[PDB]
Amino acid sequence: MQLSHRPAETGDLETVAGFPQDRDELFYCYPKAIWPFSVAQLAAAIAERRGSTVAVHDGQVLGFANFYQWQHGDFCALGNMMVAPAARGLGVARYLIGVMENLAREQYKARLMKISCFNANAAGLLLYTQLGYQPRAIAERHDPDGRRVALIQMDKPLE
Ligand SMILES: [Zn+2]
Ligand SMILES: [Zn+2]
Ligand SMILES: [Zn+2]
Image 1 (tube, rainbow, N blue to C red):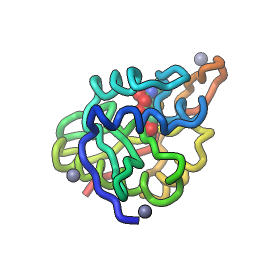
Image 2 (cartoon, rainbow, N blue to C red):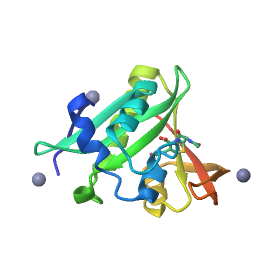
Image 3 (tube, protein in one colour):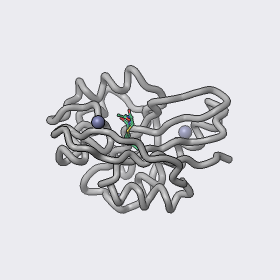
Image 4 (tube, protein in one colour):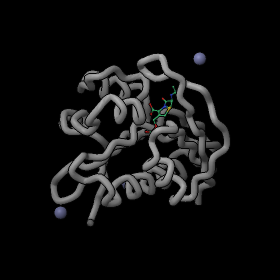
């Protein structure tokens, strides 16, 4: 499964905004967004974040991520981790997270990556655990129906 990466471009937005397949998936990767997702909502996140990057395989954009927090010499916080529905479980998020870790180290001199994952997203919790992230705290948040959820705040030292 050969993959490459590059900064996200305007032309990618419609593709990436196609990735979340339901309100749960949108909530897990962008909890401030409102279903249905849209290019305007994706562009607004890009404009206020840093490091928006796509993963590409065989001419297809298959993954997207960015940083929603960045503190030079300190840490970055990874967000908006989205994978194309036809490419789930094939290593795209693993790949892109590694790219983003290098970007945090190289550009931001980060010592730490933070990832926060909602409790219902088992696939995410297990992936981040496989990649060496450890849970540090649990924060209460609310979902779009007003129901209480647990945000599991994880981190990993970089090198
Ligand atoms: Zn690169
Ligand atoms: Zn292929
Ligand atoms: Zn509350």
